[PDB]
Length: 50
Length: 50
Length: 114
Image (cartoon, rainbow over the protein chains, first blue to last red):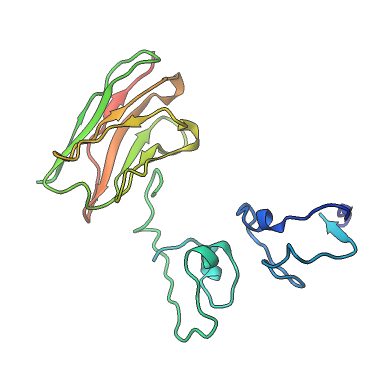
């Protein structure tokens, strides 16, 4: 957690519907996006912290 | 009805979730409330209750 | 008196084909959703299958994909379970559990693999 993996994501197609409907995630808490209506929104870059 | 432990949070108005979207959706202006009690001695059995 | 009688269990070789049966009387079977109950030496008892009302709607566990076939006698409320492509580790004792109120389960039957 103190050396969390950092990933830079862009230049591709994001399908968050499968992630939302995966049902394998105990917590899916969104502060800054809605769980739905995220497919038609896109930005300059995406940062992933694992 | 009968739900599981993490399903308690999803049974609430304005709360997102797969079950809250496909099974039981509460209205935004819902008036009333929810009473949930443990039933480990009635709805649970050795070998699995399905 | 609501009772269970078991039939079909016994010694068998891998790859056989037979009828397994739980016969119960005194109540209708389409009343609710029954399930089946398997016992093998290990951690805890392990599930196999159950069918539901308003159509067959047969459901199997992940380890039993497409092997058990069930033919079902609606006129005289009888089960018929039919086994296919048997491999060893499922040596077990079988029960069939139904709901009419109180919790009910019979005596079961023995199944072995040689």
